[PDB]
Image (tube, grey):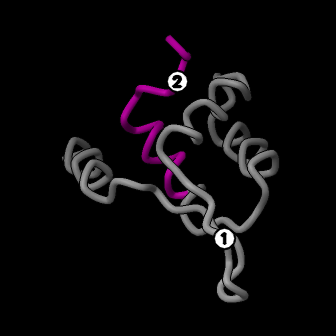
Amino acid sequence: QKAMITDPMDLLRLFDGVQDSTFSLGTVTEIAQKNLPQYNKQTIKNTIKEYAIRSSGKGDLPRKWVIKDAQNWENLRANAN
């Protein structure tokens, strides 16, 4: 049981800031915590490691993050009506 973000609206706010970010995990966390100050970095990190993945740029484009399950993401966008 590793602690994660579960509020959908919070997950959405996380995703819109992880998706396409080229920054390291560290920086990508720090930035997320600003937008989600209630959580502790480890939880954010845990959440990122869960839903996202850092590409390995074959040159282009550089290493960016993507949410692995575009489906699920769309459901969370739908739960927001």
Q: Quadrant of residue 79?
A: top left
* Residue in view at x 27 percent, y 48 percent: 72
Few, some or many C-alpha atoms within 10 Å of disc 1 (few <14, some 14-19, many ≥20)? few
Toward the viewer: 16 or 64? 64
Residue furthest to the top in view is 1
Q: Is residue 3 magenta?
A: yes
Q: Is residue 52 magenta?
A: no
The disc labelled 1 sits on which kind of residue?
Ser
Toward the viewer: 26 or 81? 26
Residue furthest to the bottom in view is 60
* Residue in view at x 58 percent, y 69 percent: 20
Q: Quadrant of residue 39?
A: top right
* Residue in view at x 61 percent, y 67 percent: 55
Few, some or many C-alpha atoms within 10 Å of disc 2 (few <14, some 14-19, many ≥20)? some
Using the image, determine if residue 1 lies above or below residue 6: above
Where in the figure is residue 11, as x and y percent of width and height? 45, 40
Which region of the structure is painted magenta?
A: 1-16
The disc labelled 2 sits on which kind of residue?
Met
Where in the figure is residue 36, as x and y percent of width and height? 62, 35
Q: Which residue is mark 1?
A: 56
**Disc 2 and disc 1: Cα gap in Å?**
25 Å
Q: Which residue is mark 2?
A: 4
